[PDB]
Image (tube, coloured by chain):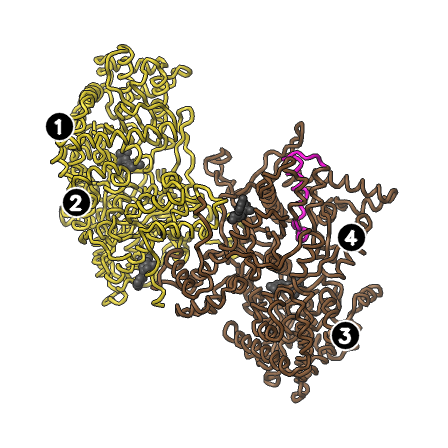
Chain colours: A brown, B yellow
Amino acid sequence: RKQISVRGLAGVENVTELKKNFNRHLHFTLVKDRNVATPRDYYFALAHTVRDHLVGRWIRTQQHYYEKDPKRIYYLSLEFYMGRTLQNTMVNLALENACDEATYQLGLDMEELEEIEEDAGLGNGGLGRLAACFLDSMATLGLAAYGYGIRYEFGIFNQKICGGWQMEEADDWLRYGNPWEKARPEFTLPVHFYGRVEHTSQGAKWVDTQVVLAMPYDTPVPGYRNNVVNTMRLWSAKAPNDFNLKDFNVGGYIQAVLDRNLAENISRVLYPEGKELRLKQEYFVVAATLQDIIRRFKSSKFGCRDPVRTNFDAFPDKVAIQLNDTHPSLAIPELMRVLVDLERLDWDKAWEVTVKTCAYTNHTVIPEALERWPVHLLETLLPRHLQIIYEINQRFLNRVAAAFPGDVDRLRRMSLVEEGAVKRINMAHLCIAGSHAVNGVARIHSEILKKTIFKDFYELEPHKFQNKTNGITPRRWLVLCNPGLAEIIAERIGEEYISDLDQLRKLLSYVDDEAFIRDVAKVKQENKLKFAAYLEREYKVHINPNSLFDVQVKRIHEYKRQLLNCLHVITLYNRIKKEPNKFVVPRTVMIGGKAAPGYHMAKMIIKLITAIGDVVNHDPVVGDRLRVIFLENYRVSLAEKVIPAADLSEQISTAGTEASGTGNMKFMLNGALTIGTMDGANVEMAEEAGEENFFIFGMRVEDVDRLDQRGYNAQEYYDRIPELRQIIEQLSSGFFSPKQPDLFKDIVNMLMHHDRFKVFADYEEYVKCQERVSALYKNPREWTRMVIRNIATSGKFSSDRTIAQYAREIWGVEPSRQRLPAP
Amino acid sequence: RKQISVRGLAGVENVTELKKNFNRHLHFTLVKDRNVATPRDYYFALAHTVRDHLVGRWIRTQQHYYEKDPKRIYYLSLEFYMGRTLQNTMVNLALENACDEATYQLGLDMEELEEIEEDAGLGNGGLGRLAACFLDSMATLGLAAYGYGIRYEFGIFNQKICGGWQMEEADDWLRYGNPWEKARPEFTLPVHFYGRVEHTSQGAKWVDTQVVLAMPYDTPVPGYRNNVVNTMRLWSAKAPNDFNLKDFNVGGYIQAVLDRNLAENISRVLYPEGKELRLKQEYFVVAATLQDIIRRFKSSKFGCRDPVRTNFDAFPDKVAIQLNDTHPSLAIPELMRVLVDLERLDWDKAWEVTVKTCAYTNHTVIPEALERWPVHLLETLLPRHLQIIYEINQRFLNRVAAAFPGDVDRLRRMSLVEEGAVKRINMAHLCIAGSHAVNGVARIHSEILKKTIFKDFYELEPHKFQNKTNGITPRRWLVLCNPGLAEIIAERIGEEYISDLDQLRKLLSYVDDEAFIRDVAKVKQENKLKFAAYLEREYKVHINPNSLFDVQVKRIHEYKRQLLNCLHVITLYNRIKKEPNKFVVPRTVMIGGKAAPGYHMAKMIIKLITAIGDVVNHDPVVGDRLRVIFLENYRVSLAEKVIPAADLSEQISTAGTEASGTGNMKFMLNGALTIGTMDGANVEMAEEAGEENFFIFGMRVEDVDRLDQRGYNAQEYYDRIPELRQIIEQLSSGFFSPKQPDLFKDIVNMLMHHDRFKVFADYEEYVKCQERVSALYKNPREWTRMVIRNIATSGKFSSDRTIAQYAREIWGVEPSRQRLPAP
Ligand SMILES: O=c1[nH]cnc2c1ncn2[C@@H]1O[C@H](COP(=O)(O)O)[C@@H](O)[C@H]1O
Ligand SMILES: O=c1[nH]cnc2c1ncn2[C@@H]1O[C@H](COP(=O)(O)O)[C@@H](O)[C@H]1O
Ligand SMILES: *Cc1c(COP(=O)(O)OP(=O)(O)O)cnc(C)c1O
Ligand SMILES: *Cc1c(COP(=O)(O)OP(=O)(O)O)cnc(C)c1O
């Protein structure tokens, strides 16, 4: 028994033991030989060779927490956007050098292999990426932490552009296996749906529930070189498969083959209204996670440390659930169902525990975005969960009246239940009620969570409102993707910045020196070259390495403002064609994102951006002064290529719409200069980088409210501005669409007659901020001089910080930059 | 490249490298650790320490085959009754001794761990088990063989007796994975169903077909210590999952959620009439194996060796295809299909090759049993294949006309098209026409196919019919299951017997040496002691390890006669209790079988065996002079546990019912006497042992044919024989059934008025033979000596013999027992 140990199984940094274990997984785990392997095989071979390294540590880390019994914190979220784990496993595990040398000797080129990896499809955007980043920084900072979510077979769509039209292909990233997960069919848990609550004697009973099974899969997450590796644990839905003869539902009728498939596809697709699948999904990931969380609390030596009921008294001293957005919110009536009905704690011992154990991050600014479910949808598949939502609610509103006696209209403003046609439940006031702390994601955004959106709750409990600004991981977003920039920096300062990012300000001391200043425009020359080849070898065009790489890689929504940017490039195209000879600083403009299937404005816009380009890029006069490029199927491993080769990071969202900008922080730290409105992220970045150092522009928040107060009359601008007048005119003539002139008709009328977001307002200012830009590119010494200052200044934008604060003010744990002994 | 070699990965019989490998797998593979591990988890680590050694050999053996280009033989069966891979994989590879040592130091019990493996639910009966025996033999004699079937996810049922009634439970054997297979997605092939045949220009084209996908799984098969490890490749059906958006069938309607369930379950269950499911499991394994077969032909250096068509002229000289019974029959219109339509050989060239490629093994006797598919089934799911079956049928019938000019009643009896209500196609006559050798499975059985069942095919082509008697492997069925018996036998004659079983004749030399005579009984005393301990510790009864373990482990049907051996147990009762103190040599009768859901007689026969024992085994007079046990859920792992432990092997079918009897042969080898009729396998086993050493009995066939010629009037026997009368009258009075007396009334009436298999007829002679049995037992020197002349005469029943004759007389290759150098 004790002879079964982790002890002899590694010669880690060793190009010869790593050549031994690559061979071991290709013939014995893959059961192939060099006579028939494929790149895919040899990548699988290599993913198990860096993985036994990771799971060597994993067992130690984990053992360590069970004998050291920290508070354990569960980050719950419905999207985890990991993307390729090979390079990140190696660079955080130290192993990249040994692996390169080893695969080299074995006559295999490790880069060609890292490009066989499928981006882990469990994310779709920001929110996903964000949790992805907090998992890194959590483990780097040694927290007893876990990420808990659904595993999505089909990701979410894979974008194809055919005809200058977006077609979504399916992403089955798992089609050939995933080398990093470990399934767990022994920890399968039941998840109950529908049914009836029979109230019997000392509780309520929820009976006749259908059931779907939650089957786990553990992917590990490695710290930065400290040998702590923690668990991400995604659930998968598996139907009961009695459905044959067993139960005697069937025999007579297998039409229940629909139980079978509707179940299995809880886990099949990410979402992408009030759907019984979304709510089915949300309940899924909460109900399994909470049985697991409770099980380590009964196990994790607290089986011994009972003193009370294996108490729930200690439950808040031992566990922390972070709800990410409102999709986790039933974590609160579900912990209240498990605690009350299953265990037996009275409602108030139970609710003490719940509030003290949860917390809720918010990411929305418009109230037309806070989740809301139909009470008839929660009565049908969740009936106990609606009674508890009602009893939480009663009790919360009795607290409210004992604070503001006689306010009546507040009792109807703060409720969980909302009345209209279709009485609904408000998922966010459920969360503020059942959390001990709420935090925004931007200072601007949590002030407006306090001041307007949740202000009566901010009066009733001011002390719940905190703020915790979002961040990026230094690792992925500078060391993995940007290694020259991480080399030259390091030369001049040290390593420690990658685990204490603000140290970057020491590079301020180098602002004039002509070393950094050429190096930086060197690396930056590197990056743009490589990628200016990727733009020919996988996808194709004729870039110009020299140019302004002008990129907005933003979700394609109206309010994100691609169309502002398409007028501007139609502006440049015009000038150069009237003035076939002006020295105009050239640009290669690169817009990238995925629409949303069935959002036809977004499908019309990616139509715009191709059609412009086919005009410009095939017109002689423009030659190679002006190229427009649509980056198909923008995603995390295209992020890490593009964001290093960029100069101009285009942040133009209407002001007030953005709650932040994580994608934003990522172009600061890789010396891209940020054009953009004074919103969300752009604010704290300008604060650090110095306003002078940032191309801030257009309508502030204020000015928009004012233009709304007097009413936005689009046409006026169209009639001052002679360029605009003409570009609208070229759009409606069919300049840019000769086969269907009429093609951009809707777009026209979008802008002219009912633009919700004031593109034509911010035009005139935009094209003059852009004039400042072209003008400063062509002064490389100073252009590059600013960049050094933006980079230097990036350290509040590191996720390690963001975590340190959830850690210190919300969770109650001191981080630790220590190295866990191990391997 | 070349440095990626199988070479440095194994210190084999090294208790220090096996423990190192256990530990890599518990931690690295399973991502478990000794705080969390379970006995299931440790068996998977042992499972894997061993598999590295297996697959090692498999890599060197398949390479070997591609560099020497042997004739590859493919065994086509829908049933492979493997049972348990681990004790068997260690013995073939010599590792049993080192793993015991190794796990013992780690302080884990290798017998504990072995008992957690699930019996590979890939079969059901003697057809499956033969195919497996053949597989161990084809590898032990250096045959370049491959076995091909379907992977059934649920097996066929698991048995469970509840109040003595059979309840079938499911067999999700695949539930915590199976660690011996390797799923190969990369090699998925489509299989086509339904459709319509477009007849265009140079060919017909099968168009508009539904497509199910066949994914392969490989399980390696080890020879006995000769280091050749061969392939079993079982197929899994998967639906194409575009079903969501892609095709534009879906969207508007997903009621084609059924294609998906009705595709998915070709691979779901084994069977268990004219069902589309069956013919769709039949074509599927055929469709998907003939492509992988024509792929190795085109690939395995015969690309090089084109000279003409990659001529399929050489196709017989390099492929051979064994259709085990009629379920692979479609391999004859599908090989012809591929070659005529896909390639473009003319009909006659293609038929030369199909006939020289295929060979049929038949296992039936009654003609009611020969497979038959209605032409409306074939016309619908297989409309090209119906066509080909018609040309084949026309043309064979024109051969027939030239041979028997003007014999018309022959033209109609030799047809593959059958005329009656429902026009059927006769899949047996298909097989004799496109195969180049038909064969029986025991000499009497070969002979009735030639004189009665296929005799006009015997007449037009006498060169085709062979015989190749069944055979059991000495490894599983003696070395593996009864190692004691192998050991005393080894002391005297060495090991060569295990790979050369005729050599057990040497044991005759020692019939009269008294060490052996006592070692043999000793051996057996152990086996029964062991077993008796199971019968209290996994199931419960009170054995008395001293009595005569009397056993029947046959399929529960009416011709298999357990009601005969029911009657006989009640006679022995009736006698111990009429005369409570006379001496009766005591027995523990054990009868086990699995009913077959839907057969009501079978189902009451086990209710019978289970209640006889309720009475006899609690009736205090009987003391321990009888006991009766229904063995729960007979499968290969209970066979290697009961078959060692027994004395008399109950082989009682009515004469003329049995073609052969794999069961039987395992009993002779493990020193058990065989009481039973002169049918099937009993014939040649009697002939090598001599009559004198067997307890043959009852109506011989020529007699059953007489009693039918005059008409078996049951009543007469019930009115001569008094003890018969007595038991019938016990059955109807409710002796055994006191709460519903009337319960065995349909058994009683069967017996009385319509037994097709003449129980009463053999009853009188039967119980007489049991008296000669008890008699001799009660004389341990001479009972042990008759036991030693059964074991010594075992030789003809070695599946290495049956294989060598297939190879030489049908497949056209030579056994070699040569060690491939390897590892
Ligand atoms: O009681 C324990 N003591 C030490 N290590 C443990 C114990 N329970 C679990 N582990 C380790 O913790 C990991 C995670 O366990 P889990 O929290 O139950 O998922 C396992 O892989 C083991 O390495
Ligand atoms: O052309 C070849 N040369 C050498 N080994 C081969 C070749 N093709 C296949 N193999 C080996 O044969 C194994 C089985 O391939 P299969 O028989 O094609 O299914 C592969 O896994 C390799 O070990
Ligand atoms: C960082 C990131 C993001 C985040 O994108 P942004 O914060 O810039 O804005 P939204 O698109 O509006 O959220 C999204 N996707 C990936 C791949 C990524 O790396
Ligand atoms: C050998 C065997 C069999 C086969 O049983 P029998 O050969 O006795 O004859 P039938 O009953 O007629 O098929 C079945 N099951 C197991 C486990 C086994 O080992």
Q: What crowding class fits label 4: few (fewer than 14 Cα within 10 Å), some (14-19), or many (20 or more)?
A: some
Label 2 to label 3: alpha-carbon separation: 94 Å
Chain at numbered mark 2? B
Q: Which residue is mark 1?
A: B692
Identify the residue under disc 4. Answer: A454
Picture coordinates of residue B566 (x, y %)? 29, 22
Residue A475: x %, y % from top left: 59, 65
Q: Nearer the viewer, residue A578 or A452?
A: A452
Mark 3 falls within which chain?
A
Closest to the camera, between mark 4 and mark 3, is 4
Q: Amino acid at mark 2?
A: Phe
Q: What secondary structure is marked by label 1?
A: helix
Camera-nearest label, 1 or 3: 1
| Mark 4 vs ligand 3: CB below 8 Å | no
Q: CA distance from mark 1 to mark 2?
A: 32 Å
Q: Vertically, is B669 above or below B4? A: above
Q: Chain of mark 4?
A: A
Q: Which residue is mark 3?
A: A718
State which mark lies toward you, 2 or 3.
2
The amino acid at mark 3 is: Tyr
Q: Are marks 1 and 2 on the same chain?
A: yes
Q: Please, which chain is the residue tagged with disc 1 on? A: B
Relative image position of residue A472 (x, y in whole percent): 64, 64
User: In the drawing, does residue B353 fall left or right of residue A449?
Assistant: left
Instruction: Tell me, yes or no, whether the highlighted magenta stretch contains residue A336.
Output: yes
